[PDB]
Length: 52
Length: 76
Length: 76
Image (cartoon, rainbow over all chains, first blue to last red):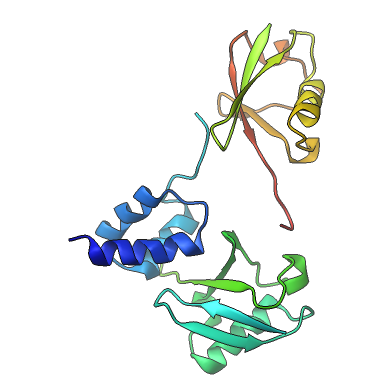
């Protein structure tokens, strides 16, 4: 389905207009909680847009 | 001026503040309406985190601006 | 020689420089070409950050090397 996952991810996408959408959906399947997902991003669990 | 705080649940809270207000006070006002502890309240603006010891003028936060409320739970 | 500078947007530019060229001078070129202020120009090479008052030979930067340009947005 991924209906609820997309809905939750999009919400975070609005909060952080500089985070990879596919990475957001990734943690959403692990934590399944916006209270921890958005936190994990701020902590540094998610990779930022770094050139390579 | 009035601003709009958007919660992860899709809730929109309207707060009447001034540019001379502090981020700490803003979060305290949210605790007055919602009850959420300011310690667990991470205010983000356009992807940037707002330091507790700052004002709205520091991040150029104007009226009707969207404030992102991020949560945090470190248990390991 | 030629060097490649890549921005956070994925954009990659080629700059004409020489070993005797200074990082401060190189960043000045980017300042005129892209319009990015040197105060917000953070040049990283091999994980290490390069200093302004240094030459390309100081870090043994060879031709066709890729440098990472990170910006410093504070107060916005």
